[PDB]
Amino acid sequence: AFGHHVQLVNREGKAVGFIEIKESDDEGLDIHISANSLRPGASLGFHIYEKGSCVRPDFESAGGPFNPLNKEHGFNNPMGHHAGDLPNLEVGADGKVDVIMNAPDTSLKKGSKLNILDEDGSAFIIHEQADDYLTNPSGNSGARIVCGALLG
Ligand SMILES: [Cl-]
Ligand SMILES: [Zn+2]
Ligand SMILES: [Zn+2]
């Protein structure tokens, strides 16, 4: 079961839902993401970045794609695949998303190369537009608009 609660904040620092994570059996991690205040009906880029720091207003700070296998971006890229690349989120008429997805190339185990919960942590970020699953570095998914820091 599902732990490591992370609070999601938007560019204006408002709380806009949460993520929790299960070490799956298996494999990789299952990510339960339940967010609100997003653009009704949009497909939005959604990735794991290499530092657990969510500082307004652009979240540059930080980092990273989470990319321990040094690949380039995108499911569709013949030279793809960052480990922190996740499917687009599909926002309801609601403006909400509430789904569980699998992130097969990640782990929470200390000493795994795919461990996202290192000393520096990681960040889950939702982008303003759809990831095209091909362009580097981030699929042309535009601005980072929601961020949740995973620390520990
Ligand atoms: Cl990315
Ligand atoms: Zn990527
Ligand atoms: Zn849920």
Image (cartoon, helix red, strand yellow):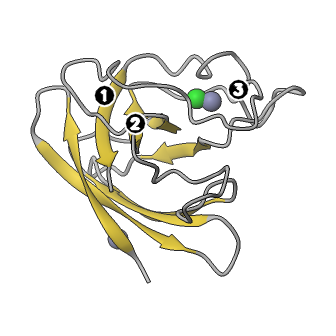
CA gap between label 1 and label 2 equals: 6 Å
Looking at the image, is 46 positioned above or below residue 105? above
Q: Amino acid at mark 1?
A: Ile
> Ligand 2 appears in which quadrant?
top right
Query: How would you rate the neighbour count of disc 2 (Cα within 10 Å): few for under 14, some for 14-19, many for 20 or more?
Result: many
Q: Residues within 10 Å of mark 1 (few under 14, many from 20)?
A: many
Numbered disc 1: secondary structure? strand
Residue 106: quarter of image: bottom right
Q: Verify CB contact (< 8 Å) between mark 1 and mark 2.
A: yes
Residue that label 3 marks: 73
Please give left or right for residue 6 compared with residue 77 in the image.
left
Q: Which residue is mark 2?
A: 126
Q: Position of residue 140 (x, y in %)?
A: 57, 16
Is any atom of residue 104 visible in this view?
yes
Residue with the mark numbered 1 = 145
Q: Looking at the image, do the residues carrying marks 3 and 1 touch, with CB atoms under 8 Å apart?
A: no
Q: Nearer the viewer, residue 118 or 49?
A: 118
> Which of marks 2 and 1 precedes in the sequence?
2
The amino acid type found where label 3 is placed reads His
- Looking at marks 3 and 1 on the same chain, the residue that comes earlier in the sequence is marked by 3
**Dot 2: element:** strand
Q: CA distance from mark 3 to mark 1?
A: 19 Å
Residue shown at 35% from the left, 18% from the top: 60
> Which amino acid does the dot numbered 2 rest on?
Ile
* Quarter of the N terminus within the rendering: bottom left
Does mark 3 have its CB less than 8 Å from ligand 2?
yes
Q: Is residue 123 above or below residue 115?
A: above
The quadrant of the picture occupied by the C terminus is: bottom left
Of tags 3 and 1, which is closer to the observer?
A: 3
Q: How far apart are labels 2 and 3 at the CA level? A: 16 Å
